[PDB]
Image (cartoon, grey):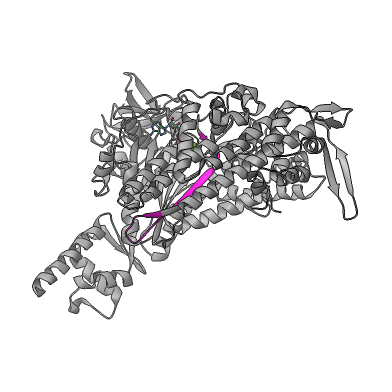
Amino acid sequence: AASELYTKFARVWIPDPEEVWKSAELLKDYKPGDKVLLLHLEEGKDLEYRLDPKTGELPHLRNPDILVGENDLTALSYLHEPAVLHNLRVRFIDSKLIYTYCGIVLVAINPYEQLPIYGEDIINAYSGQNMGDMDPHIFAVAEEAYKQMARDERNQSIIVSGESGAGKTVSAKYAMRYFATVSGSASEANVEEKVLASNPIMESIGNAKTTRNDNASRFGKYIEIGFDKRYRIIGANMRTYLLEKSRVVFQAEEERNYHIFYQLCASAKLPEFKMLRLGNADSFHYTKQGGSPMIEGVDDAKEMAHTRQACTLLGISESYQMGIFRILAGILHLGNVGFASRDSDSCTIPPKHEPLTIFCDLMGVDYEEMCHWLCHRKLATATETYIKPISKLQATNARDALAKHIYAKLFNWIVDHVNQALHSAVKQHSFIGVLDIYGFETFEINSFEQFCINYANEKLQQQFNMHVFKLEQEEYMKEQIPWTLIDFYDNQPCINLIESKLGILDLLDEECKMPKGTDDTWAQKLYNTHLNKCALFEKPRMSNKAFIIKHFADKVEYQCEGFLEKNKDTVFEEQIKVLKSSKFKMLPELFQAIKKTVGHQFRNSLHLLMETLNATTPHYVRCIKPNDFKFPFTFDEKRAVQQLRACGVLETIRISAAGFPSRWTYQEFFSRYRVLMKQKDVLGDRKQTCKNVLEKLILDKDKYQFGKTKIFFRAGQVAYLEKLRADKLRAACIRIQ
Ligand SMILES: Nc1ncnc2c1ncn2[C@@H]1O[C@H](COP(=O)(O)OP(=O)(O)O)[C@@H](O)[C@H]1O
Ligand SMILES: [Mg+2]
């Protein structure tokens, strides 16, 4: 039947290597059996488009001009890939609209420009309205979640997704503002202020500049915002995920360490900071490696003022704040300690070194002991102790490991205190969860950190697909309702390759058991186990030190060096002991106790989170990066199309197009709509009673369908039944009155 639409003047989409899809118009009517189409391109040139001799499949028809730039993609006549790309291009380039709906899921595009599209009057304008009675915006999602939590008394979750830089961090912040405003009616409104204040604090400690993002979010965050019976904020709790430790000691060619170090170095001249004995960021190796200590459009000194102000608002006094700056200053002074070689396998550090002097002074430690333990290691046996001198390379490695460890304890200490400030005495009626996770990334060189983040992103896709596609269509099959299968790309195989008993993480952990274990040996074990036995896993022709894996977004090559070390993540017992013995109270609090590998800990942490998400009603936001140049309102078609297919956008709209998301059991429907039924319509069979009543209430049979155990409805029909229920109760009250 679709071939009847291929008439003279009809428009179609044809594949193009650079533009992905090109629009063309038919110069003649198509007849079944024709091998070439005479097309007029929009550039003024005529083309003979040859059809496939085996399949005879025609190019995609283009939707009418009235359907260009629609608020909801389900309004399109032809629901195919070229149509999606065109509709989003027009709304972005022409209309400057960043938002579009794909049913319940929201699509967000990064503008690379500040626009005033979120005044409190806008917040008020989105408040109190229906879905679609406002145009697409993040506030609509927030309001829908607010509306659902209040009516359903069910916890909700806001899940944002996308590759690095797509606007995801930005989206979560604005959603929180909406809830804080509505809740703002409270007496102890300071709690909402504290909740919003949490974000900039974590950004200072948690973010750093990458080539992808000037403010990359190098840890994960999940926030539960609790509500009372009044549907007003009671408090909150943050659960966070693995921070990039390698960032403290290393930075690439145009990257920085965490923002807070630069804020502290910018404030070195102030009298309060004088005790720290700091200089500019160029003086310390841990800050200098990147080659550029400043971010354009950012004033580190100004940010330092804001960060301090944020700390005081949470109730963190100046003594606490000066205490954290001391730790950070100490990490910088440790980074420039001079270490000299003795013979081939020994090292020595002088008790005279200027940087180690202030390090020992700030930490409240003995210089002579630190010189000894940076140069030697202890081996303890039941009967005796043995000492091994360390090489120059080992001394610097030992020093750096301690720096990562200190920074890690410090980050955790801060989040614990914000959670203490965010705590609530009252009982939780319900909650809204917000997820903010580092997005898919790739570089010239990729390591263990990229492996972990990509693996986490794979899990998010699995949760999304399980809920949206898998769980949902399986129900229709069991329900015995006419259903056409909707295809999706299932990533379960790569997930098994990573997580299963035979998986990559398990093999790395087994290599960690062996003292003889090596990255080379592990890579060889991966090749032996999977080189030609697996389709998701492959090795490049030129290398034996790296491997490539097929993720949902793209294939990624990972270098094997450092994987066992990074999986172990440990520090010498003597160094931790000298810090446990420190004179400064904060250091002993971290070093006091306030076997599984980082990879094992990471898997379970993600499992607990997946389980947590499954308990709530999800609300998904898909963020897209339009261009790599960071330019205002520029659209890259090749780059966009790959993100759309990776996100499964088209199939999400096709499943949405099938409709019937709402589903009442015959018992629930009967119990809720008994008032719309006359006593004569109530048969011994509840199922037949519901059929007879629904057939009387709704005349169009295309708006509802009957399954084995549930009744299915099209959009707006339950609201119509609620209007009828409300009208019947009102009429009954008037009759009684
Ligand atoms: N509302 C916005 N207005 C302007 N630029 C934005 C907006 N949202 C995101 N961006 C741009 O996208 C970049 C990355 O988005 P952000 O949410 O900050 O981090 P990410 O998207 O990586 O989570 C920002 O640095 C900024 O350049
Ligand atoms: Mg981010």
Left or right of 497 on screen, residue 682: left
Residues 701 and 575: in front is 575
Tell me if 335 is positioned left or right of 411 in this view: right
Residue at 58% across, 36% down: 325
Q: Is residue 471 left or right of residue 336?
A: left
Q: Position of residue 63 (x, y in %)?
A: 29, 36
Residue under the image location 85 percent in, 47 percent down: 379
Quarter containing the C terminus: bottom left
Rendered-image quadrant of the N terminus: top left
Q: Residue furthest front?
A: 271
| Residue 590 shows in the view | yes
The one of 563 and 119 positioned closer to us in this rendering: 119
Q: Decide which of 537, 206 is in the foreground and name it.
A: 206
Whether residue 102 is visible to the viewer of this picture, yes or no, is: no
- Is 631 covered by the magenta stretch? no
* Prevailing secondary structure of the magenta residues: strand
- Of residues 309 and 379, the one nearer the viewer is 309
Q: Is residue 397 above or below residue 589?
A: above
Name the residue: 63% across, 31% down: 445
Q: Position of residue 344 (x, y in %)?
A: 88, 29
* Segment tinted magenta in the rendering: 216-234
Percent coordinates x, y for residue 237 in the rendering: 48, 52
Residue 377 appears in which quarter of the rendering? top right
Q: Is residue 264 left or right of 663 when viewed as pictured?
A: right
Q: Looking at this rendering, what residue extends furthest in the top direction? A: 44
Where residue 153 appears, as percent x and y from the top left, is: 35, 62
Rendered residue at 20%/76% (across/down): 681
Give the number of marks.
Answer: 0
**Residue 398 in which image quadrant:** top right
